[PDB]
Length: 52
Length: 53
Length: 269
Length: 49
Ligand SMILES: *[C@@H]1O[C@H](CO)[C@@H](O)[C@H](O)[C@H]1NC(C)=O
Image (cartoon, rainbow over all chains, first blue to last red; front, side):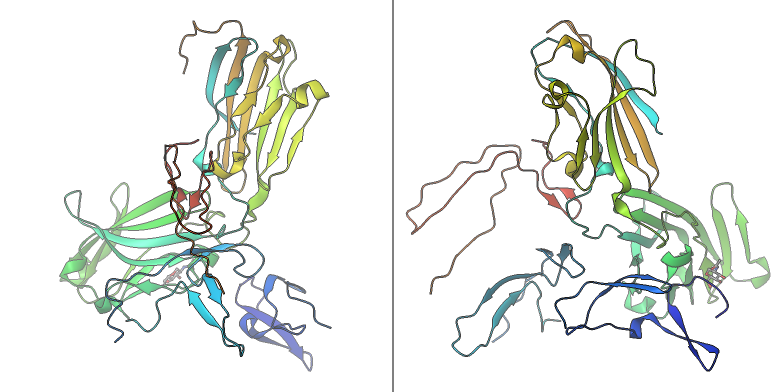
């Protein structure tokens, strides 16, 4: 929130209020739980098998 | 009766895919499997030494 | 660019194979990304040359600290995110008589294989008004009252130690050739070798067919040039350029290759 | 079902290894030259080639 560049958290808005949360809780799935590799701002990279 | 593992020591083996693509010299690295059972149960030989304190 | 290391003259017979020896353990990489961002810090305590240092606590990049002594649990504390800001300082919650001595904070980069260490001298007093931190000329010396915590500062703000980048593959080795009469900067490239394995040779087939480097070049950091079937047109100033741009290794070696003679060479360098 | 018994490979450092003729069923041995194996902390062998 205070415009640092820390490597622990993330921002998410609710009712035009910017709240904070943890990188370790986010996840992406196609069918299997994917693996997060590259994490930068509004961008995420993943490498995970054939899901529909 | 399980007092056979006295002077043992675990490994660091050459895991081909440690996740995220590449290889790792990893301790969880599996070396050999055997699937002789007729009902899908799997007997696995991993580079850890579990149960031992 | 780079800096010079060895600027030698090599005399060999025509028709033989030239070997321009170029070796470096700090340019090693493999066809894997196997802990290629692995660093380790560790705190050791010693008491001079005639005492044995003991490992107290060590730490891998992006992890949580592991303590070696059960007494030292909840007593020696490091910042678990030391590799984000380069603040590797160690807090001792409560000191005793076994803790007096010189502490070394050791930074090690396993990928570039560089090692660096710093010392701090601990003296434990009884009066708190004598407690100070001063510079003895080459290391910080802290005098701390017994039972008080001790913050032994270890701060290294170099970019190579933090978790910011470490995109490894930008090491590159260049093989250059300077023909006689040809001025510098317009030298023809002989080989470009990327850590991933890709090679670029330049020139007509007569040069490309005869220029090779051993297939384990980047794996062992030996980029020695092998020139098969030496011709008179091969003479000149050859240069091996080893570049590990992220960890700041930038070296070149220069070989003055003259082909005249098989046996009566003088040993240079 | 068979079981492929594969022991640890004999890395002959700074030397040339020699195959010993055993009477095992489907006994297989092969000596590969110019190997330079790497471990966690670098080369297992002191010699280069
Ligand atoms: C480094 O860590 C110590 C330990 O508490 C802390 O007091 C200090 O403020 C830190 N400095 C920086 C620049 O993070």
